[PDB]
């Protein structure tokens, strides 16, 4: 009947229609001929910068759309203040080629970008975001101050709080503010003479950049990287995070006493720093944000990916499993105990964390909330379903519709 | 252009040029991706173009394209369509077509096996009774006392203005699901509807959790008929665990043969509404989905309690622990009973090899990532880290409506 995607839950038998996808103004990577939904970074997901501001016609339409979004969210659509704000944006773009967001618009926009993020299972929390306005920042040194404050506020001694800090937007003929690091906290990856890697192989490139830029390298598996911070039209400067600001959790297992002897650990705060926050056509190239971890990010991906710390076989050996045959399920067994250790250790340390069952259950609640609020919720099934125990969580059995809404967090090319 | 396809574990890149051979729309558009949907939402020149394409594929496959046999065959097909609005395949074409359809199935992790498929031609079938005989033979052949062999049996194609041959059951082997008026379901809840259909066509029910269903077989424009399978035909494996002695006490079992029987086989524009096929099980189908899905047997909590796990909270990972042991028991029991089965690690490793074979052979391979990645331990398998392109190639296996 309804001219919209029909969405089914196969556990419960229930049916919804997504009308929200009608609001999408940007194409994704799929066509009637082939689905490219499993691609991490298709050409249709990456952006590209250009030294001059967008066609004013293009900016204006994106801006008017956002201003409309804003005035709706405060139930003043069609009002005199709504129309005057539009005029003010048209005028500002007409004379300068760009415009600026009021503070409450920036707050609404940051929350909406999170709410719109199809790959995030944590969106039940979308309305609880502390927005630090840093659009006054004028130096790399000052970015560091703002970032340290963010870290202190967000970490809160283990009672984590979601936050984003927004640095000045891209400007016509002026260099970007950029944080070179992909996260505020990253372990070094040192390429050994044998070709193997000590530390986190995900971080080889950023490690060597830090070294090129004068950082004296350690040689551990868990060396915290310094930040490479870039103010407009300047070489990036190097900043060492004071160790007491970086909360870490040593990993131990509730019953396997040898696990603590492994010397594994992870940091408390997942703070992503290389993403572009786009609002009403405005581009915030530096806008780091943080929440708290879902345990599978640490226990399954970062610790067990073959191209990350790759500890599965080591743990399986300690567990005395048969690692000579796939059918012993030694990988599945070790992976479970590693995830358990992550959960147990974070709880012991009083550091906020959520397991993949609690997380996906809460994401189902989010889906129902959004069905009523907006008539749908953009969601990337492959990313929402956790990397272990897929069909054991409710999201596996939930069909999802994926599409791009703005405000958005977007990937952007590396500054170098 | 053509999609750049990357493996994130190895850093290796391919380009899929095979997708350009797709003449059939999937559900996605540039505005929104619908890849996670289980089912699709919904003259004679068209048939003729599909027929030619397929005949071309066939003669290319035996490397005799442009031959006299090739040109004469195209003319036979064209003459037959022009006069009758349809045509018929030669057995060798059908054997090639059935293998290609499996090969092209984006949701199948077992495609390394695609060239090894026994094709039974059952197109000279005129009655439900004859359908039953063919099905029993298929089952006997494919089961092979536990040394499972992949097979397909192809019943007569659809013809305009006449009902289809259909097997109403979704698989040749299904356990009954009896709806207890106290809300619940005894047996397999996936099969409540077929179970009830059987009863009202005269089946005398059981009351167990694992009662094997009769087949409802339908010849064109006739009520379906009921046929009970001879119990010696249905090989089953009692489930036990290698170390937890209490596991056997759960009374769990599963059948050996995954024989799917409700899909439509399309070859060269011709449609085969009954063409049941079978291979062997990947252990997660049974251990994870069939036994642990909340809307299937849903045994996670029973096993967890037996394992004395803390059910009170998600963060004990009781679900994950119990699932692992359930999958282990399935593997162990099948291996003990000498019945073919493949674990999800071995299966995904073979599929990676298959992807590489196909890249060299065809320049790509249609794959549905969400269906290829197993339902436990996803990122622990190599397929999780492999980008895939999904598209429809013909010959194809397709869904079709239930005939009731
Ligand atoms: C509050 C607790 C939160 C949890 C448990 C959570 C969970 C997750 C997880 C598990 C992922 C997948 C990441 C990966 O596999 O690499 C993800 C992705 C994402 N998250 Fe959330 N998140 C939280 C808060 C936030 C916040 C505060 C923001 C932004 C304001 C955010 C925005 C995003 C975005 C944009 C992605 C897509 C990542 C990408 O494409 O690389 N999340 N989240
Ligand atoms: C030889 C051993 C085989 C293995 C291990 C295997 C494995 C699998 C698995 C695990 C699935 C997903 C099923 C689900 O989750 O419901 C699947 C789907 C599928 N398989 Fe294979 N398979 C095998 C043989 C075959 C054969 C012989 C055929 C056809 C001749 C075939 C055609 C298909 C098709 C069409 C699907 C899609 C199912 C659907 O969309 O409902 N497979 N396979
Ligand atoms: C290497 C790579 C990785 C990724 C995913 C990173 N996603 C991390 C992330 C982002 C936001 C998060 C928010 C909360 C949270 N707990 N984890 C979060 C983790 C995408 C593209 C590329 C590339 N190229
Ligand atoms: C409820 C439902 C389920 C499905 C997937 C069934 N897929 C079974 C299947 C098919 C082929 C197989 C081949 C081999 C094998 N081991 N298992 C195989 C299992 C599709 C549509 C609906 C609907 N409506
Ligand atoms: C190839 C595939 O897209 C890739 O491995 C994806 C799959 N799903 C994911 N899901 C999450 N949450 N995070 C990821 O990095 C990925 N990686
Ligand atoms: C909604 C989602 O597409 C659905 O639950 C899918 C996910 N992946 C799957 N993968 C396999 N192999 N089998 C399935 O039934 C499903 N179900
Ligand atoms: Zn798609």
Image (cartoon, coloured by chain):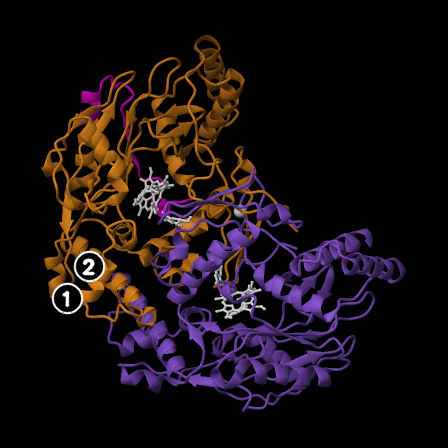
Chain colours: A orange, B purple
Q: Residue placed at 19% from the left, 35% from the top?
A: A151
Which element carries disc 1, helix, strand or loop? loop
Q: Residues within 10 Å of mark 2 (few under 14, many from 20)?
A: many
Q: Position of residue B11 (x, y in %)?
A: 37, 45
Q: Residue furthest top?
A: A95
In the rendered image, the quadrant that contains the N terminus of chain B is top right
Q: Height in image: A265 above or below B223?
A: above
Label 1 beta carbon within 8 A of ligand 1:
no
Q: Nearer the viewer, residue B85 or B195?
A: B85
Q: Position of residue A127 (x, y in %)?
A: 35, 39
The image quarter containing residue B166 is bottom right
Going by the image, does B354 lie left or right of A208?
Answer: right
The image quarter containing residue A360 is bottom left
Are the residues tagged 1 and 2 within 8 Å (C-beta)?
A: yes
Q: Residue placed at 63% from the left, 67% from the top?
A: B263
Q: Nearer the viewer, residue A302 or B69?
A: B69
Task: Count the numbered circles shown.
Answer: 2
Going by the image, does B50 lie left or right of B175?
Answer: right
- Of the numbered discs 1 and 2, the one sitting upstream in the chain is 1
Q: Position of residue A261 (x, y in %)?
A: 10, 58
Quickly name the residue at label 1. A256
Quickly name the residue at label 2. A341
The answer to whether residue A79 of the structure is visible from this angle is no
Q: Verify whether residue A399 appears in magenta.
A: no
Q: Residues within 10 Å of mark 1 (few under 14, many from 20)?
A: few
Q: Verify whether residue A125 appears in magenta.
A: yes
Q: Position of residue A26 (x, y in %)?
A: 52, 33
Q: Which residues are magenta?
A: A119-145
Label 2 beta carbon within 8 A of ligand 3:
no
Q: Residue furthest right?
A: B83
The answer to whether residue B301 of the structure is visible from this angle is yes
Q: Height in image: B359 above or below B120?
A: above
């Amino acid at each position: 009947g309804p001219k919209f995607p029909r969405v089914k839950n196969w556990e419960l038998g229930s049916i919804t229609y997504d009308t929200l996808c009608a609001q999408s103004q940007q194409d994704g990577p799929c066509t009637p001929r082939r689905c490219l939904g499993s691609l991490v970074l298709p050409r249709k997901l990456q952006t590209r910068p250009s030294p001059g501001p967008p066609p004013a016609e293009q900016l204006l339409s994106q801006a008017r759309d956002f201003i409309n979004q804003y005035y709706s969210s405060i139930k003043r659509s069609g009002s005199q203040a709504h129309e005057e704000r539009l005029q003010e944006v048209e005028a500002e773009v007409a004379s300068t080629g760009t415009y600026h967001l009021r503070e409450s618009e920036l707050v609404f926009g940051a929350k909406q970008a999170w709410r719109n993020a199809p790959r995030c299972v944590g969106r039940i929390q979308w309305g609880k975001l502390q927005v630090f306005d840093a659009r006054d920042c004028s130096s790399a040194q000052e970015m560091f101050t703002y970032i340290c404050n963010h870290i202190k506020y967000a970490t809160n001694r283990g009672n984590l709080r979601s936050a984003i800090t927004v640095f000045p937007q891209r400007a016509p003929g002026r260099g970007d503010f950029r944080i070179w690091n992909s996260q505020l906290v990253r372990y070094a990856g040192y390429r050994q003479q044998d070709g193997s890697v000590r530390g986190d192989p995900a971080n080889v490139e950023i490690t060597e950049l830090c070294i090129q830029h004068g950082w004296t390298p350690g040689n551990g598996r868990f060396d915290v990287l310094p930040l490479l911070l870039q103010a407009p039209d300047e070489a990036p400067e190097l900043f060492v995070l004071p160790p007491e600001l970086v909360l870490e959790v040593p990993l131990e297992h509730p019953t396997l006493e040898w696990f603590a002897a492994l010397g594994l650990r992870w940091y408390a705060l997942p703070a992503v720093s290389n993403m572009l926050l786009e609002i009403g056509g405005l581009e915030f190239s530096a806008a780091p944000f943080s929440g708290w971890y879902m345990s599978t990010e640490i226990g399954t991906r970062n610790l067990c990916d073959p191209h990350r710390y790759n500890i599965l076989e080591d743990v399986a050996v300690c567990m005395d499993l048969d690692t000579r045959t796939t059918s012993s399920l030694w990988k599945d067994k070790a992976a479970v105990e590693i995830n358990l250790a992550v959960l147990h250790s974070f709880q012991l340390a009083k550091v906020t964390i959520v397991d993949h069952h609690a997380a996906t259950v809460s994401f189902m609640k989010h889906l129902d909330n959004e069905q009523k609020a907006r008539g749908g919720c953009p969601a990337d099934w492959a990313w929402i379903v956790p990397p272990i125990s897929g069909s054991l969580t409710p999201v596996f059995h939930q069909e999802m519709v994926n599409y791009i809404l703005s405000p958005a967090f977007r990937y952007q090319p590396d500054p170098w």
